[PDB]
Amino acid sequence: FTLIELLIVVAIIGILAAIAIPQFSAYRVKAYNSAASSDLRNLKTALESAFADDQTYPPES
Image (cartoon, rainbow, N blue to C red):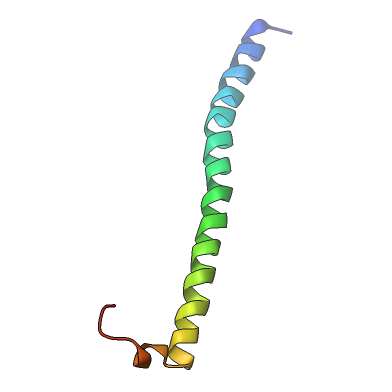
């Protein structure tokens, strides 16, 4: 019933949200980009190792 309860609830949740939205938006972004980059790295380096691809190229081309 007191405005003190409302002030505290809006304060604590105000901090929780203000950090959560950017931190979590950029988290799902960096997870998309971590998995995306590592997909293009891990499968390509495996292809170059399995077929021994570097054999047909000069040192640091």
